[PDB]
Amino acid sequence: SPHVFISYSWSSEDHKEWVLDLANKLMKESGVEVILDRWHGVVGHDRFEFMENSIKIADKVLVICDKDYCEKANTRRGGVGTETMIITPNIYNNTKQEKFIPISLGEENGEYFLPDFFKSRFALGWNYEDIDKSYKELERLIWE
Amino acid sequence: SPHVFISYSWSSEDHKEWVLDLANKLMKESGVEVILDRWHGVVGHDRFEFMENSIKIADKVLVICDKDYCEKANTRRGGVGTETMIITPNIYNNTKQEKFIPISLGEENGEYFLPDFFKSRFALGWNYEDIDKSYKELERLIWE
Image (cartoon, rainbow over all chains, first blue to last red):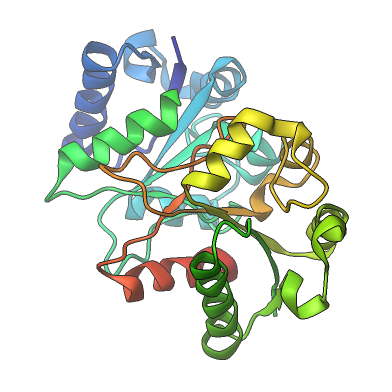
């Protein structure tokens, strides 16, 4: 099975629910073993360590790039500090590049959200009007 | 400006013309420096070494993945002929991964053509019904 860690920001309760629904769906319908912070009982100050360690054991890393994740990633408001949950340039540059599957949420005109330090600009443009098509491509990016 | 090498096979005269048109368009409309075999006068059995040298100086590498390219890549892998400009497992694995911009041609149902040894499964699904959208995204993958 693909081991898939999901990197995401707790932008809101609805967004946490969208990520949780995606994790449950990947586990149920796609035979993927999702590494999710909510399913490991990760306390606030253990978040950076959990993200760091999870990326090394995961086969794929979903980068949930909504607007809040991308400008938190680009600015790094105080820098790393255990709280973090957002991939840093250092983590990105010490990870095999093929693991990352950026998913852009809420962009317009195909200007997919993606942190500036991602050298490859590919991202799965999530189609809210065609979920099944976007989910199919996510399965291909994970499995194939 | 980005130096963009185009990896493609001479599958047919129409396909060579499609790649030639794309190369001309990228230079004219997107201000990129395209490294094209026909513009350097690379004759058939010199093409593979030309691909190797060009990928080292190129900023991006477009992988024109139609059916013929992907089946020869999947079947022959590192054993592709000296006359070919088809990426091998060694070339993919020994090149900075962000260079590669695979373009899937002629795939159906979102089952994008891509050699199986490409560790990252991302590819630009070329939309023959919305070229401007596909060219917009190709420009972004090259520039951004």
